[PDB]
Amino acid sequence: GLVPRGSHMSGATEACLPAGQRKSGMNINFYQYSLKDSSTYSNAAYMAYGYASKTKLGSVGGQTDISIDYNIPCVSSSGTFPCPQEDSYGNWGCKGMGACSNSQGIAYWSTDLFGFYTTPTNVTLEMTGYFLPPQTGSYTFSFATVDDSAILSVGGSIAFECCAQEQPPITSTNFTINGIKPWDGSLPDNITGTVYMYAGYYYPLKVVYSNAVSWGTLPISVELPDGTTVSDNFEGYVYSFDDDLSQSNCTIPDPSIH
Ligand SMILES: [Cl-]
Ligand SMILES: [Cl-]
Ligand SMILES: [Gd]
Ligand SMILES: [Gd]
Ligand SMILES: [Gd]
Ligand SMILES: [Gd]
Ligand SMILES: [Gd]
Ligand SMILES: [Gd]
Ligand SMILES: [Gd]
Ligand SMILES: [Gd]
Ligand SMILES: [Gd]
Ligand SMILES: [Gd]
Ligand SMILES: [Gd]
Ligand SMILES: [Gd]
């Protein structure tokens, strides 16, 4: 027919067309999270919005390299160097450094997380921005692994509301990737979620990430409709806009018919 019929039962993901000045990269907000608290981040409500009820520590904007790979220090015979988790051994040492004198179980201060000076051993962060598909089709987002707890949400009224990136978080627990740390046990690696996206619309994107102890890890990728994979560096794909709650036409509830 003259027009497409639309995704079945309004199934299209909501997207946005913000009219303001586009900024490269995502905004990162940092919130307090307690060292060795292995229970708070196991709740869907906390990971969707509850994190923002705790003290906000600070923020950084314009971040395009969004994967997390935080390594604790090994205080070694030859100085203090970050230890890759797979190189830690015993009680404890780091391969190529010998025995480490420092505890794995205390807070450590570092700018490793997006240049913001904080405790990557124990913190919760929220990444917000808009994903711009250059190609129409199915996109598969993935976390290679999650240490400790994380979610990824895509879509208007799922990640956040259109033209309202900076507002308090919305309550949706309809996660695109549920990487919430289970009450007992661990999640597989390569946890994934797929979204069908229309080229040139801006899709709200939220990642909430938490760590309680020592190493923190969140390697983020997306597989494009063309079968190629973008990992870590999302430059050219992720953007921010200042709130404009007055832009009436900003929400596109169904990009398949717009
Ligand atoms: Cl270090
Ligand atoms: Cl060694
Ligand atoms: Gd990176
Ligand atoms: Gd980097
Ligand atoms: Gd890092
Ligand atoms: Gd690593
Ligand atoms: Gd870094
Ligand atoms: Gd680094
Ligand atoms: Gd880095
Ligand atoms: Gd909404
Ligand atoms: Gd951890
Ligand atoms: Gd594929
Ligand atoms: Gd890097
Ligand atoms: Gd703003």
Image (cartoon, rainbow, N blue to C red):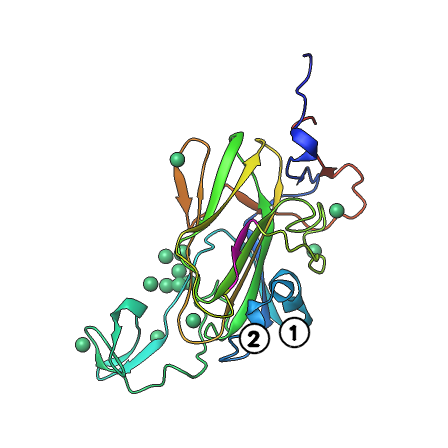
Image: 199 above or below 63: above
- Residues drawn in magenta: 176-180
Which quadrant of the structure image shows residue 195?
top right
Q: Which residue is mark 2?
A: 33
- Nearer to us in this view, 218 or 27: 218
Image: 221 above or below 87: above
Crowd rating for badge 2 (residues with CA inside 10 Å; few <14, some 14–19, many 20+): many
Q: Are marks 1 and 2 in contact (CB under 8 Å)?
A: yes
State the SS at label 1: loop
Q: Is mark 2 within 8 Å of ligand 11?
A: no
x, y percent for residue 196: 56, 35
Crowd rating for badge 1 (residues with CA inside 10 Å; few <14, some 14–19, many 20+): few
Question: What residue lies at 56% left-to-right and 49% top-to-bottom?
Answer: 176
- Which numbered disc flags the more N-terminal residue, 1 or 2? 2
Can residue 147 be seen here? yes
Quarter occupied by the N terminus: top right
Q: Which amino acid type is shown beneath numbered disc 1?
A: Lys
Q: Which amino acid type is shown beneath numbered disc 2?
A: Tyr
x, y percent for residue 159: 64, 51
x, y percent for residue 52: 66, 67
- Which mark, by number, is residue 54? 1
- Nearer to us in this view, 46 or 67: 46
Q: Is residue 177 magenta?
A: yes
